[PDB]
Image: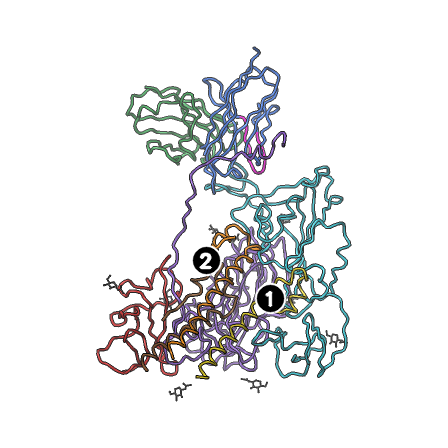
Chain colours: A purple, B blue, C yellow, D orange, E cyan, F green, G brown, H red
Amino acid sequence: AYTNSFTRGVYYPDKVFRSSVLHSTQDLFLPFFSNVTWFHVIDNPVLPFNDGVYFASIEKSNIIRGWIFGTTLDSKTQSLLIVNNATNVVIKVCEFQFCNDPFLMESEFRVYSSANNCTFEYVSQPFLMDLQGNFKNLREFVFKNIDGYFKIYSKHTPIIVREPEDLPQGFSALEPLVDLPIGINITRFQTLLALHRAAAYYVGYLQPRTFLLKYNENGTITDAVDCALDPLSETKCTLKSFTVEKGIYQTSNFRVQPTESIVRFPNITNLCPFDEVFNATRFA
Amino acid sequence: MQLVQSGPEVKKPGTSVKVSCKASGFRFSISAVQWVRQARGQRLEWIGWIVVGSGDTNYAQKFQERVTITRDMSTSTAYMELSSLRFEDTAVYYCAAPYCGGDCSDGFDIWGQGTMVTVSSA
Amino acid sequence: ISSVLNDIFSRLDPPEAEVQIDRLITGRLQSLQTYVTQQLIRAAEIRA
Amino acid sequence: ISSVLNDIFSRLDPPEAEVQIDRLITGRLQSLQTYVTQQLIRAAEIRA
Amino acid sequence: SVYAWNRKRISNCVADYSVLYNLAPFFTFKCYGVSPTKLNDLCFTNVYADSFVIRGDEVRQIAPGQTGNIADYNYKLPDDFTGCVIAWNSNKLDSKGNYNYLYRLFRKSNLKPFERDISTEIYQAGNKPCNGVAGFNCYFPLRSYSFRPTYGVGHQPYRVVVLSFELLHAPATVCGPKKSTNLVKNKCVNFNFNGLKGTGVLTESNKKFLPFQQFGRDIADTTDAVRDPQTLEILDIT
Amino acid sequence: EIVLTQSPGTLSLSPGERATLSCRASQSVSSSYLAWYQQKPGQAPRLLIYGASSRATGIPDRFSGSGSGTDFTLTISRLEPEDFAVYYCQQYGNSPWTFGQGTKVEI
Amino acid sequence: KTSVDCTMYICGDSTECSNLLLQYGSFCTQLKRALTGIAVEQDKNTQE
Amino acid sequence: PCSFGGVSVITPGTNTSNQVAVLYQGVNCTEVPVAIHADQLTPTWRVYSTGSNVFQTRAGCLIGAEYVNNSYECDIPIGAGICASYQT
Ligand SMILES: *[C@@H]1O[C@H](CO)[C@@H](O[C@@H]2O[C@H](CO)[C@@H](O)[C@H](O)[C@H]2NC(C)=O)[C@H](O)[C@H]1NC(C)=O
Ligand SMILES: *[C@@H]1O[C@H](CO)[C@@H](O)[C@H](O)[C@H]1NC(C)=O
Ligand SMILES: *[C@@H]1O[C@H](CO)[C@@H](O)[C@H](O)[C@H]1NC(C)=O
Ligand SMILES: *[C@@H]1O[C@H](CO)[C@@H](O)[C@H](O)[C@H]1NC(C)=O
Ligand SMILES: *[C@@H]1O[C@H](CO)[C@@H](O)[C@H](O)[C@H]1NC(C)=O
Ligand SMILES: *[C@@H]1O[C@H](CO)[C@@H](O)[C@H](O)[C@H]1NC(C)=O
Ligand SMILES: *[C@@H]1O[C@H](CO)[C@@H](O)[C@H](O)[C@H]1NC(C)=O
Ligand SMILES: *[C@@H]1O[C@H](CO)[C@@H](O)[C@H](O)[C@H]1NC(C)=O
């Protein structure tokens, strides 16, 4: 099942303060009006983890608690673990043998049989923090891995309608949360869904784009445009304004890209005798 | 893609001899080299083999106190020394290694031209 | 390296920070020069 | 060293190609500036 | 060992670098993006120090943008490194002969910057699978060093420590000793907040900074607000 | 120690015919490693069928090879006057790696 | 009436050069503005 | 060098509508300038050509507008004697 993203998933790109300005970054974001997968439970595949993932959830009681990452999820390579128990949160980059049954006040070791070579641990206040009905919890997250760093963003917001259960309108940015100096290679990803005996979660992959952010006078990002969605949006980007006047504007060129590569060195194979250049009996 | 071997050489009994195998035309940092001796008109015989990068060796039981198969990454050659020669050691010595670019070829399909050594006293 | 001269001084070392200083100074000078030229050309219009 | 960017970066290393690339880039920028300034000056003739 | 290198976080600590010059003559002290002498004037974030031990001639392989066995299978710095480097020839400690220092030798493809590969599985150089036993086209990755004395400087043991510290002062944690005067407001005064410098008039402010959101900035990209470290007030610099 | 008994000793077909050989082994050897070779007189040998089924590069499709366990055969479809040599079979599964005896194909 | 491409002119089919140029400033924005103004005015003259 | 050229976007102002037309400068409409499948920058843009959209002027290929056969005063100039406007 697929549904469409609807301009969601921006995060504060840097830790400075700005106000009444328009800013143009370039980083890894979720493209506007994208195509996200859709899962329902009353399903825990092993999904690929490309450059990055966007994750959301619409859910009353926390049926889902935490994630696991890793390149093979067996016990020959390292792999993460984030489990959010009743009062805290656990992170281990340690070595694991994950049990095929991943579901978790049940046994925590229900996920893994044994652990060795444990590398980097961390405990702190738990991620699930939402404050009776008349609404539903909408948690959103971003996970990204560059140059040996793992970074987590976050946000949450009560929602109004439950009828379509599709991503609602609006605009809310994701405050930075944590940065981890782990040291691994990530390709695959799976969620830890805990059933004891009514929730939906989505997935969208990140790409390199360019956005034009707007900050109000309080200092919050209340709007943005994708500089590559369509000609109007790139016109707005190049004029640095959310409004375009009547006329004909010239924006950017177009270049056909190369297909392959070519190498044409000459076809001789000897070795020039460096062995008397160095190793000569008598230097003059 | 080829191996070049040393030249013919005659020794007197009791001495020691050193044979060398050139290497050119492929990626030598991964391959392995084995040594095979064949007398005149007889079957082939095995001696031992070496993995280049690690340097580890392995020998036949008979050739256990007379062979030292060592290589040298710098010039990209593999060497073999035979000690305490006897009359029975006169044969032709070959050198073989798998073709190995990004991956090795799962079989020794590069064979040197073979060198001769005569253990005599005249 | 950066765009803050006090930053460049506090990081680099005066034998090898002045190179960056020269880059910065040259660029700012070019900016001013272009500005003044455009003002001259526009004043010609307004006088006409 | 040369006027070909690909050659400059083929021969030199990144910690040493930046000075040469800087020189080339500034020169081309200057040529463009001359062209634009000349055209602006010369369009006033045609307007008059 | 180089193939599984340790790493230690530094935080919440007045860190001086005067002490470390008190060593045997460093075979190397390079500092790649900041001069070593003025290292007591800056406030950093998240200083990270990670250590290992290697052989003599390979010490010049620990630098941005180089290739070679260590640099592509064991430890790789990124191109835009920003930190210092130390190395100091321990042969009075790590040589007797010693054989529990290890390093990788075979691998499918090169590493990525700042990545640790720890697995010990049989390398398979061919198209046909191995069943966990060595053989033709089936090797073991690791190899021991065997640092015996009297090998000369080329083959003598060497300790190494590299420091990487990100340099934009987000909420600062580690920085060197310096006194602290009482702050004055509404007077043109030389200031030096946490690492900034320059003159201005520090006043009260009305802006609201998020907990991660430490110093503001303006159109021309110059600091114009700051969270005073001790008393977490928000000031305006004009 | 693996001992290979290459039989028959000598085989005498006329050109254009069908030829078969054999490498019966003492114990069992993994089919992963076993190779046939062709030794022209006065030459180094060369690799024909490595891995017990796969042909080496640049070899006519006449040569097949087959079998696993303890029996391996090599069949030449049609006999042309340049296939008259001495053929060896070598295992390199476990140490020591040992050869065969030879099998001369003549007119 | 003419027009110009900074990237194609300075940075001949090289990507490193484009990445290094994009941190200079708004020089091409300025040049494009100037040439566009000249070009429009040329149509205005014939109209008048 | 591989083919390249400029692009210009015709809009009535966001305050009225969001439809745009695109003019490719100094190319030929016959060959599809974008060559949709071919990798190029301006990537997400797939203005799929139809019967009404394509129209070749002297300035270049103009994709996204239909050529009526009346005459009006100029509204948004394009070049070579052809204008454009937003009308029923
Ligand atoms: C991270 O791990 C994955 C697999 O664990 C590696 O992916 C392999 O990449 C090579 C090179 O393209 C491919 O030929 C393989 O098919 C990939 N394997 C799989 C299972 O997809 C990846 O190379 C590793 N990254 C690093 C930097 O070592
Ligand atoms: C999402 O993907 C499906 C099939 O992969 C496709 O039919 C659908 O049109 C896509 N949605 C969008 C908005 O592209
Ligand atoms: C949650 O985990 C922490 C750390 O392992 C532990 O101290 C705490 O008691 C756990 N809470 C519950 C309710 O088990
Ligand atoms: C990891 O733990 C296992 C436990 O048996 C051990 O064999 C292995 O050597 C350990 N790895 C390291 C690098 O010590
Ligand atoms: C900005 O902050 C002021 C005071 O904190 C508040 O009155 C005003 O409503 C804020 N602006 C917005 C758009 O919330
Ligand atoms: C010391 O610092 C703490 C917080 O870091 C602060 O609350 C306290 O007022 C400071 N003491 C001083 C400035 O004397
Ligand atoms: C937007 O359009 C409305 C008519 O729909 C008009 O009254 C208004 O003035 C316009 N505003 C701007 C900023 O163009
Ligand atoms: C486009 O191509 C057609 C046929 O190839 C030709 O008739 C026409 O003149 C071309 N247009 C231009 C501008 O060259």
Quarter placement of the N terminus of chain A: bottom left
Judging from the image, what secondary structure is the residue with disc 2 in? loop
Give residue A27's position: percent from left, percent from top: 51, 66
Magenta highlight range: B47-58
Q: Note whether ligand 1 is within 8 Å of mark 2.
A: no
Q: Work out whether residue E1 can be spotted.
A: yes
A153 to E2, vertically: above or below: below
Q: x%, y% of residue A229?
A: 41, 70
Q: Quadrant of ligand 8?
A: bottom left
Q: Indicate the position of residue E175 as horizontal and vertical percent values.
A: 71, 66
E223 relative to F82, above or below: below
Which residue carries the number 1 mark? C2
**Quarter-wise, where is residue B87 in the image?**
top right
Residue D11: x and y in percent read 52, 50
Q: Amino acid at mark 1?
A: Ser
- Judge whether residue A96 can be spotted in this image: no
- Quarter of the image with the C terminus of chain A is top right
Subunit that carries the residue with mark 2: G
Residue shown at 38% from the left, 54% from the top: A259
Question: Which amino acid, mark 2?
Answer: Ser
- Chain letter behind tag 1: C
- In space, the residues marked 2 and 1 are separated at their CA atoms by 24 Å
Under circle 1, the secondary element is loop
Disc assigned to residue G14 = 2
Q: Is residue B54 magenta?
A: yes
